[PDB]
Image (spheres, grey):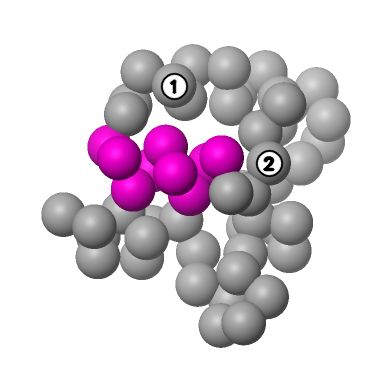
Amino acid sequence: VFNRPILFDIVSRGSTADLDGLLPFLLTHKKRLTDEEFREPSTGKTCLPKALLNL
């Protein structure tokens, strides 16, 4: 289970280890990293801006 707050926390902390199970979740559930569930409702900021800002 990868919800948006958890994914943002992981990507902001830079924990690359916690992303191993993301691939089976995305493949099995037919979910994509560009889906609305993975975007901030306020701005639409995606995970990559989160990671780049939190350097």
Chain part drawn in magenta: 6-14
**Farthest-out residue, left:** 55
SS state under label 2: loop
Q: Quadrant of the N terminus?
A: top right
Q: Is residue 17 rendered to the left or right of residue 1?
A: left
Residue 48, how many percent across, how many down? Answer: 38, 57
- The label shown at residue 3 is 2
Residue most toward the bottom?
43
Q: As rendered, which of 17 and 5 lies closer to the eye?
A: 5
Q: For this view, does 54 lie left or right of residue 40? A: left
Q: Position of residue 17 (x, y in %)?
A: 36, 18
> At x 16% / y 54%, what residue is drawn?
55
The reply to whether the magenta stretch includes residue 22 is no
Amino acid carrying mark 1 in the image: Asp
**Left or right of residue 19, residue 11 in this image:** left
| Residue located 24% across and 65% down the image | 53
Mark 2 is surrounded, within 10 Å at the Cα level, by few (under 14), some (14 to 19) or many (20 or more) other residues, namely few
- Badge 1: few (under 14), some or many (20 or more) residues near its Cα, within 10 Å? few
Q: Decide whether residue 8 is among the magenta residues.
A: yes
Amino acid of disc 2: Asn
Who comes first in sequence, dot 2 or dot 1?
Answer: 2
Query: As displayed, is residue 39 above or below residue 51?
Result: below
Distance of label 2 from label 1 (alpha carbons): 13 Å
Q: Nearer the viewer, residue 12 or 27?
A: 12
**Predominant SS along the magenta part:** helix
Residue name at image x 36 percent, y 65 percent: 49
Residue 11, located in which quarter of the rendered image? top left
Identify residue for label 1. Answer: 18
Tell me the element at label 1. helix
Answer left or right for 20 relative to 1: left
- Tell me what residue is drawn at x 68 percent, y 75 percent: 41
